[PDB]
Image (cartoon, coloured by chain):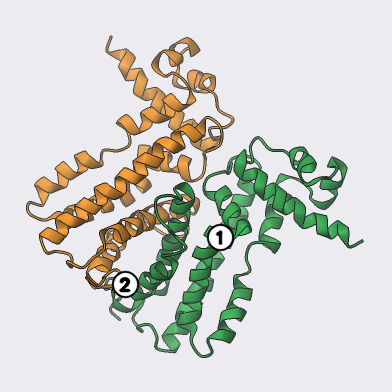
Chain colours: A green, B orange
Amino acid sequence: KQEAQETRQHILDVALRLFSQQGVSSTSLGEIAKAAGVTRGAIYWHFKDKSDLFSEIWELSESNIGELELEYQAKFPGDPLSVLREILIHVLESTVTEERRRLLMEIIFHKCEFVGEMAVVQQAQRNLCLESYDRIEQTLKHCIEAKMLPADLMTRRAAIIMRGYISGLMENWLFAPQSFDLKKEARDYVAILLEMYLLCPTLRNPA
Amino acid sequence: KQEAQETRQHILDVALRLFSQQGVSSTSLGEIAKAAGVTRGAIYWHFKDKSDLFSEIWELSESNIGELELEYQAKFPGDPLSVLREILIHVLESTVTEERRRLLMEIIFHKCEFVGEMAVVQQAQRNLCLESYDRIEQTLKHCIEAKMLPADLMTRRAAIIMRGYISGLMENWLFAPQSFDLKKEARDYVAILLEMYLLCPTLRNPA
C-alpha cells in the first residue's frame, strides 16, 4: 503493498515541483528519483518515460472537472448556469492557492519544451482541447434549454471565447503574480464571462 | 557597410524560425550561424549572447504598436475607440498570417525555456507587461473623455481582461490551428471585447 502507491503520487508531486524550478528540458527521471527519496530502478517501475510521467498528471491530479460538476450540481439543483459559473470560479482560484493546480499550469504556459518527446503530449492535449469545446458547447446548450442564456447564442463562438478568456487570465497571472490578484477577483472575472453571453451582441446571429 | 545590417535582420529571421522547430533550449548561436549563411565569428559580433539575440526581437520586429497607432489615428480622426479596435484586429490577424508575428508568439507560449538565462528576458517582459497595463488604461481613459465608454468603467479591471482575452485567443490558436479560424473571426472577437465595457455590469462600480 500500500506504501508503493503512496510513493507513486509523491513522484507526481516532486516531478511537478522540479519541472517548475528548472524546467523539463534539463530534468531527467534520475533527478526526480533522488528528490522524492527513491531509487532510479523504482521510478522507471511506476512510469515508462518522460511522456508517461507527464501524461499521468492529467489522470489523477488534473481533470477533476467532471467531479466538480457533481459537487456544484448537488449545491445548485436545476441551475446549469451557476454550475458553469462555480466551476470557473474554482478553476481561477485553484491556479492561485492550490499547489497541484498552480504548478501544473506553470509548466505548459512557461516551463515546457513542446519540441521533441514533448510534442507527443502536445498532440495528447490537442484532442483534450478539441473535446473540451464540444463538452462546453453542450453545457452552453443545457443553459439554452433552461432559457438562462439567449436562444440565438452561438455555442461554437462562445466555446472559443470561454477557453481563451479563462486560460488567458491564468497564463498572465503565472507570468506576473504581483500584477493583479486573481483569487480575490475570480468571482468578478467569471461574472463578466457570464454577462457576455446574455447581453453582448455579435455573439447573436440571424436565422 | 550596408549589407552587414542586411544580414543582421536575417539572423533575427533565421533564429526566430529555428527557435520554433527545435526550441531555444537545444539551439545555440552556432546552430543559427550555419543556417543564415554566416560564420560563428560574425554572429557574436552582432549579438552578445542568448538573451541579447532574444531581446533584439522586440526592438525591431515586435512592438510596432505605437506606429500602428499613428497608422489608424490618421485613418480615424477623433475616434479613440476605433483605434483601440483596429490595433486589436491587426494583432489577432498578424499572429495568423504574418511570419514575424506568428513565430515570435509561438516561442513565448510554447517553445521557450523561462528557466536559466531565459529568466532574464522573462523579467524584461515582466516590466513590458506592467507598463502595458498603464498604457492601455490611458487609452481607455481617452475613450472615457470622449464619452465612447461609460464613465463608471474600471480601467484597471479592463486592462487585466483585455490582455488576458487577446493573448489567450492567441496562445490557443498557436496550440491548435485547426480548431478555429482566428483571422476570419478577428473582427468578431474584438467586437465582443469592445461590447464588454459599454454593456456588461460588474465592470461598473459605485462612487
Q: Chain of mark 2?
A: B
Q: Report x, y in % for residue A138.
A: 50, 78
Q: Quick one: SS at disc 2?
A: loop
Q: What secondary structure is marked by label 1?
A: helix
Compared with B152, A153 (above or below) is below
Residue B161 rendering spot, x and y as whole percentages: 35, 59
Give the answer, above or below, for where B169 lies relative to B74: below
For label 2, count other residues whose C-alpha is less than 10 Å away and answer few (under 14), some (14-19) or many (20+). some
Residue B184 seen in this snapshot: no
Residue A97: mark: 1
Residue at 63 percent of width and 62 percent of height: A62
Check the image and report above or below for A122 versus B200.
Answer: above
Which residue extends farthest right? A1
Which residue bears the numbered disc 2?
Answer: B202
Q: Is residue B190 above or below residue B48?
A: below
Tag 1: amino acid: Thr
Kindly report the distance in space between the C-alpha atoms of the residues bearing marks 2 and 1.
24 Å
Q: Is residue A151 visible?
A: yes
Kind of residue sitting beneath label 2: Thr
